C-alpha cells in the first residue's frame, strides 16, 4: 500500500499552489496544445436547419511543466472531477449551435497526468455544429461541412493548436455509416486567422459529405418519372372518342401534386429550384402540355387530324427524352 | 414492434487512441413482431394489387371504365407508399418494404400499359 | 518572477470591490 500513499502525496503536491488563472509557461513561448479527435458517429444531417449532429471523443493534449512528477513510473488517471482544478484551453467551436458533454453515469471526461508533464484531457462531446448548405444541386449535391475549433481569449502568442500526428489525429471516420450520406473525404487544416485584436489559432476539421443518390433515386425521382411515363400512355388511346384520354391525363397532375406535397415536408425553402424542384416542375410542365396537346387536337378535329395525332405521339417521347438527358447531364456534373 | 428473445453478455478488450479498455456489451436478442406492419401495410397494398386484377377481369372495349379503374388504382398505391415512408429512416438501403411497394407499383403500371397496348 | 507580479495584481483587484453596486453609484451614470 506504499504506492497508494505515494500517489496521494504526489497528487496533493501537484494540486497545491496551482493557479488555474495562469496558462502553462505564462510569460513565455506559446503552449503547444496538441489536439486529437475520434468521431464516434454522425447522428444526423439536418439540412432544414443546415447543421449536423456529431458525437466525438474530443481530446486535447498539452504540456504543463508544473504538473510534473518523477517518483512513480506510471501515468496517473485522476477522476474527472479534478479537471475544474486544472488549467484548460478555452477551446470553443466557432460553428456550434448546440452541444453538451454526456453526463451518464458520471460526467464523461478524462484526465491523465503523464510523468513528463503532458496532460491528456479529453471529453465525450455531442455537437450540433452549423454547416452552410448550398442545396441548389440537391439531391445531387456534395455538401461540404466543417468543424471550426478555435481558442476564444488566447492569441497565437500564448496558445497554439496542432494535430498531434499529421493525419492520425482524426480517427474512426471510415467506420461511420451515415444513413443518407457517404463521407467521401475528410481533411484537417491548421490556420492562423488574423482578427482585429490579433492572430488567433484555428483548426478546421472538414467532411466532404456526398449525398447517397441510391436512396433518393427511388424515394423521389422514381415515382415522378414513372408518372411521366404514364402521361405518354394517353397519346395511344384514340382521337375519335377520347373522353377517357382527358380523364387519364388530368389524373396525372393530381398524382404529381400529391407527390410534391409529401416531398415538400422534408425539404427547406431555398428559392433556387434545386435539382429536385426543377425536375418535378419540368415533369409537371410536360404532363400539363400533354393535356394541352389533347385540348388542341380535340378542338381542331371537332372544329389532317390523324397526322396531328401521330406527330404529337412521336414528338412527346423524344422531347421528353431530350429534357431528361439535359437535366441529368447538367446536374450529374 | 419486437420481442425479447433473450439476452447475451460479452466482455472483450478494445484498443483506442487513449489506451486499452475493457468493454462490457449486453446483447438483447430482439425479434421482429411483423403482425402490426402486415395488417397496416402488406394487407391493404396486396388488396391494391388484387384491385389491379379486377381491372383485368373487366372486359369489352369499354374504354372509359378501363381507364378510370387503371388510373384510379395508382393514386391509392402512391398514398400507401407515402405512408410506409414515415417509419423508414433515411438509411441508404434497399428496404424490403420499399421493394414490396415498388413491386406493387410496377405491377399496376404494367397492368395499365397492358390495357394501353390491348386498346 | 513575471507571474508573481501578475498573480499579485489579480489578487489585489477584487480587494474592497462590492459587485452589488454599479461603478460610481450616486456620483455619475455608468
Ligand atoms: C505513459 O506515458 C508514456 C509517455 O507519454 C507513454 O509511453 C509510450 O509508450 C508507447 C508504447 O506503445 C510508445 O510507443 C512506441 O514508442 C517508441 C519509442 O518512442 C520514442 O521515440 C520516438 C521516435 O520517433 C519518439 O517520437 C517518441 O516520442 C519517443 O521518444 C516508438 O519507436 C514506437 O514506434 C512504433 O512502434 C510500433 C512498432 O510496431 C508501432 O506499432 C507504433 O505504432 C509505432 O509506429 C512506438 O511509438 C511511446 O513512444 C511512449 N511514449 C513516449 C513519449 O516515449 C505511455 O502513454 C505510458 N507509458 C508507460 C505507462 O510506460
Ligand atoms: C470543405 O470546405 C473547406 C472550406 O473551409 C475546405 O477547406 C479548405 O481546404 C483547402 C485545401 O486543403 C485549404 O487551402 C489550404 O491553404 C493553406 C494556407 O495557404 C496559405 O499558406 C501560407 C500561410 O501558411 C501563405 O503564405 C500562402 O500564401 C497561402 O495563402 C495552405 O497552406 C494549404 O496547403 C497548401 O496550399 C497550396 C496548395 O494547395 C500551397 O500554398 C501550398 O502547397 C500549401 O502547402 C491549403 O492549400 C483552405 O485553407 C481550406 N479552408 C477554406 C477554403 O476556407 C475543404 O478542403 C473542403 N473539403 C475538402 C475535402 O476539400
Image (cartoon, coloured by chain):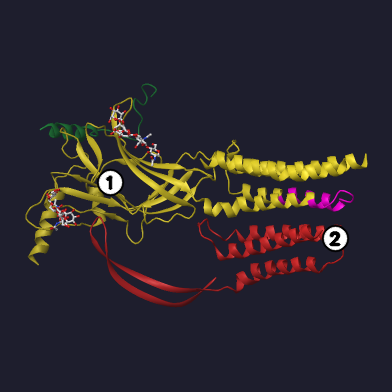
Q: Is residue A8 above or below residue A144?
A: below
Q: Do the residues under discs 2 and 1 have CB atoms within 8 angstroms?
A: no
Check disc 1: other Cα within 10 Å, few if <14, some if 14-19, many if 20+. few
Residue at figure coordinates x 69%, y 41% from the top left: A319
Q: Nearer the viewer, residue B23 or A78?
A: B23
Q: Which chain is the one coloured green?
A: C
Quadrant housing the C terminus of chain B: bottom right
Q: CA distance from mark 2 to mark 1?
A: 68 Å
Q: Which residue is mark 1?
A: A167
Circle 2 sits in a helix, a strand or a loop, which is it?
helix
Circle 1 sits in a helix, a strand or a loop, which is it?
loop
* Residue A251 painted magenta: yes
Q: Which chain is the one coloured yellow?
A: A
Chain B, which colour?
Answer: red
Name the spot of residue A329 as percent of width and height, x first. Answer: 56, 40
Q: Nearer the viewer, residue A21 or A233?
A: A233
Name the spot of residue A199 as percent of width and height, x first. Answer: 28, 29
Amino acid at each position: 500500500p506504499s504506492n497508494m500513499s505515494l500517489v496521494k502525496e504526489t497528487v496533493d503536491r501537484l494540486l497545491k499552489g496551482y493557479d488555474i488563472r495562469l496558462r502553462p509557461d505564462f510569460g513565455g513561448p506559446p503552449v503547444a496544445v496538441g489536439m486529437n479527435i475520434d468521431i464516434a458517429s454522425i447522428d444526423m444531417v439536418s439540412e432544414v436547419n443546415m447543421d449536423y449532429t456529431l458525437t466525438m471523443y474530443f481530446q486535447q493534449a498539452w504540456r504543463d511543466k508544473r504538473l510534473s512528477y518523477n517518483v512513480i513510473p506510471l501515468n496517473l488517471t485522476l477522476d474527472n472531477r479534478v479537471a475544474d482544478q486544472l488549467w484548460v484551453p478555452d477551446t470553443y467551436f466557432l460553428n456550434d449551435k448546440k452541444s453538451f458533454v454526456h453526463g451518464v453515469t458520471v460526467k464523461n471526461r478524462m484526465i491523465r497526468l503523464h510523468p513528463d508533464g503532458t496532460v491528456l484531457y479529453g471529453l465525450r462531446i455531442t455537437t450540433t455544429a452549423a454547416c452552410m448548405m448550398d442545396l441548389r444541386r440537391y439531391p445531387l449535391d456534395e455538401q461540404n461541412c466543417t468543424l471550426e475549433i478555435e481558442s476564444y481569449g488566447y492569441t497565437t502568442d500564448d496558445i497554439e493548436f496542432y494535430w498531434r500526428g499529421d493525419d492520425n489525429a482524426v480517427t474512426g471516420v471510415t467506420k461511420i455509416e451515415l444513413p443518407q450520406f457517404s463521407i467521401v473525404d475528410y481533411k484537417l487544416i491548421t490556420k492562423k486567422v488574423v482578427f482585429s485584436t490579433g492572430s488567433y489559432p484555428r483548426l478546421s476539421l472538414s467532411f466532404k459529405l456526398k449525398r447517397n443518390i441510391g436512396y433518393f433515386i427511388l424515394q423521389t425521382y422514381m415515382p415522378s418519372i414513372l408518372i411521366t411515363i404514364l402521361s405518354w400512355v394517353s397519346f395511344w388511346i384514340n382521337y375519335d372518342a377520347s373522353a377517357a384520354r382527358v380523364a387519364l391525363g388530368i389524373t396525372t397532375v393530381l398524382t404529381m401534386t400529391t407527390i410534391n406535397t409529401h416531398l415538400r415536408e422534408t425539404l427547406p425553402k431555398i428559392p433556387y429550384v434545386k435539382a429536385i424542384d426543377m425536375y418535378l416542375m419540368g415533369c409537371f410542365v410536360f404532363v400539363f402540355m400533354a393535356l394541352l396537346e389533347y385540348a388542341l387536337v380535340n378542338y381542331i378535329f371537332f372544329g389532317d387530324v390523324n397526322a396531328i395525332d401521330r406527330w404529337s405521339r412521336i414528338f412527346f417521347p423524344v422531347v421528353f427524352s431530350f429534357f431528361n438527358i439535359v437535366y441529368w447531364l447538367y446536374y450529374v456534373n | 414492434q419486437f420481442s425479447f428473445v433473450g439476452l447475451r453478455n460479452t466482455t472483450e478488450v478494445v484498443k483506442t487512441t487513449s489506451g486499452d479498455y475493457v468493454v462490457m456489451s449486453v446483447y438483447f436478442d430482439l425479434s421482429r413482431r411483423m403482425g402490426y406492419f402486415t395488417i397496416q401495410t402488406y394487407i391493404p397494398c396486396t388488396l391494391i394489387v388484387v384491385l389491379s386484377w379486377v381491372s383485368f377481369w373487366i372486359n369489352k372495349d369499354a374504354v372509359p371504365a378501363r381507364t378510370s379503374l387503371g388510373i384510379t388504382t395508382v393514386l391509392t398505391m402512391t398514398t400507401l407508399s407515402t405512408i410506409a415512408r414515415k417509419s423508414l429512416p433515411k438509411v441508404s438501403y434497399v428496404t424490403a418494404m420499399d421493394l414490396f411497394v415498388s413491386v406493387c407499383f410496377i405491377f399496376v403500371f404494367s397492368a395499365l400499359v397492358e390495357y394501353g397496348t390491348l386498346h | 518572477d513575471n507571474t508573481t507580479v501578475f498573480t499579485r495584481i489579480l489578487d489585489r483587484l477584487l480587494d474592497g470591490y462590492d459587485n452589488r453596486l454599479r461603478p460610481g453609484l450616486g456620483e455619475r451614470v455608468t
